Image 1 (cartoon, protein in one colour):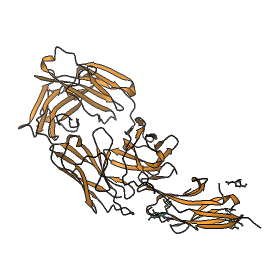
Image 2 (tube, chains in turn red, cyan, purple):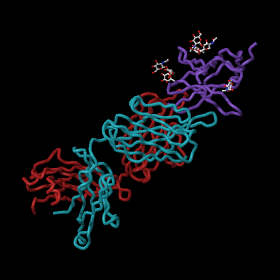
Image 3 (tube, chains in turn red, purple, brown):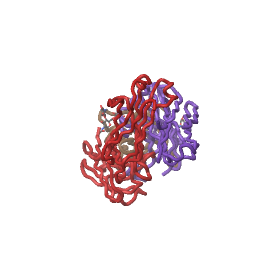
Image 4 (tube, chains in turn blue, brown, purple):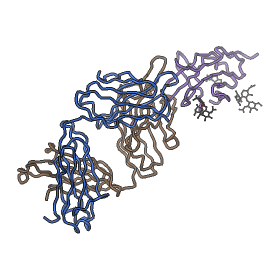
Amino acid sequence: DVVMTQSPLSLPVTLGQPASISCRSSQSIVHSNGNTYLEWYLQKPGQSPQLLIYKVSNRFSGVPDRFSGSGSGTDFTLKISRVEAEDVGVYYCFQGSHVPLTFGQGTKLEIKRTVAAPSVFIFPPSDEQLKSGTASVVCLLNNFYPREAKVQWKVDNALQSGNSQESVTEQDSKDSTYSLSSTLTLSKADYEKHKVYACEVTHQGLSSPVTKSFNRGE
Amino acid sequence: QGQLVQSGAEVKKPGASVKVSCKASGYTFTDYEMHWVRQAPIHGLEWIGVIESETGGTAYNQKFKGRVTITADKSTSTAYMELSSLRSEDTAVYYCAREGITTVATTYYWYFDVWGQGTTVTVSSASTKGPSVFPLAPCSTAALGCLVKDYFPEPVTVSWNSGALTSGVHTFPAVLQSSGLYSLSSVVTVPSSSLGTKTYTCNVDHKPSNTKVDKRV
Amino acid sequence: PWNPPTFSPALLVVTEGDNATFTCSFSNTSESFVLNWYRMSPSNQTDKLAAFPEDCRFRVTQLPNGRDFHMSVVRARRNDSGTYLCGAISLAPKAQIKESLRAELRVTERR
Ligand SMILES: *[C@@H]1O[C@H](CO[C@@H]2O[C@@H](C)[C@@H](O)[C@@H](O)[C@@H]2O)[C@@H](O[C@@H]2O[C@H](CO)[C@@H](O)[C@H](O)[C@H]2NC(C)=O)[C@H](O)[C@H]1NC(C)=O
Ligand SMILES: *[C@@H]1O[C@H](CO[C@@H]2O[C@@H](C)[C@@H](O)[C@@H](O)[C@@H]2O)[C@@H](O[C@@H]2O[C@H](CO)[C@@H](O)[C@H](O)[C@H]2NC(C)=O)[C@H](O)[C@H]1NC(C)=O
Ligand SMILES: *[C@@H]1O[C@H](CO)[C@@H](O)[C@H](O)[C@H]1NC(C)=O
């Protein structure tokens, strides 16, 4: 099967600047009729993919001027002359010259924004959940940028591992920030044998890591 | 152009089968082929197969050939897609997409100009269970929230003060826990001065289990 | 049209009772395809007679090479006379329908 590889996989770009995505095919994708059915699709957040570029360099109807494609052999490139806000999403290259038809793995285009330090909150386990035998501790990172952030849980200064899941929101359409929720899942047994619970947050917007804590009880 | 509308979400046990439809309108059905495409995080976008409505001819990706059947009813402009012997890894969004048939009267250089809205198929051994809603309160800006825990399947909808409170609300995507159940947190940022003035209530709606919970924080 | 199938002979005449065999040659490029045998009814309405793969008086037979096909009417009748053709339907990669030129079958009276 023809394998389609995209580069890069994450593309943050400032509003108004150019952007470029590379696509490489593991072999030639010339069709037996001589045509090269290389295509570029864009999947805006929460929507279906839509066709951008057909046959290597041809712009589909309704697609703005700033999009353009090019390539030769196994190397193809998608260029955006000026990145606009409505251009965020996942970009896929696609080949239709050989069966099976294959897509690239995707390139997420995000807006590069000025750095924003997160606001950190911590929530203790509730009365009502503790009566259910389980204990959940939530650490919230609100409205930060860039996406890369480290959250480490410490129970009585013991660094936890394996007992925490986390989820991040899509980049906000109005301020271009992310939000993250870390969830320390402990048995109520384990919860009631320790006292202090903290999450340490490392991020480019924080000159030094931030810690939010609470003592079980107080 | 035209339109493609697919059938609703589906949840099935491992080893079962699912059949999803795709209704076309706004264009001539027989002028086009109908493809089926899968999207899952472990898999990316992958092509399943294609049917030509007039002849009933089909072509399948060797990966799915043997456990997928694609059918089309030209009289009702509907294409179908039946996946048998479902595995947990078949959990994905399933799209249908048209492709212009090149003829001596018309030449099509592109593939997928119109797509359906997608159909969610979740394959799991878990059983339908409504969520346990718990408050998230701290021990000049305060944060409050709700922990929506141990529910199946997706989705739930969380609203604050019955839709009145939308500013500063963050509902995070659900994460599949080791128990095969989903967990989700929804938070909101309020001024600290309003902690004793206003009432802040979550509205958790879980249709598959017929569950509505109104939880105040 | 790109890589159409050919349908031969352009004019085939047989005596009523005999078998009539056409040759439709299709050199496929990538084998997700189906071949259909058609007869053109009053003022260009097409009737499907048989299809490869998959009335039993109309037989399609694939020959050893990957190109030639035999389309035979068994015991041709007087009203089998008409216009025939073969169409190739490539499903993937890149959907395309390509027809042959029309051929004529004439069925004459037996003495
Ligand atoms: C006319 O054809 C019939 C049926 O033949 C089929 O189609 C042919 C075009 C060819 O592809 C054959 O291989 C196919 O079988 C013939 O009927 C056969 O008659 C013989 C007589 O002994 C009999 O043994 C066979 O069983 C018959 N065929 C079948 C499928 O049962 C017929 O002989 C042909 N007419 C003449 C005179 O050529
Ligand atoms: C051109 O097509 C032939 C025939 O393919 C068969 O019939 C088609 C209608 C379709 O149903 C195919 O799936 C069938 O295989 C191809 O010949 C076969 O090619 C396959 C390649 O995987 C091979 O395994 C078989 O042994 C071949 N059998 C015969 C009888 O030829 C041929 O490969 C195709 N040519 C090109 C260039 O694609
Ligand atoms: C042709 O004639 C035959 C003779 O019985 C009969 O089937 C019918 O009248 C005609 N059929 C077709 C298909 O033309």
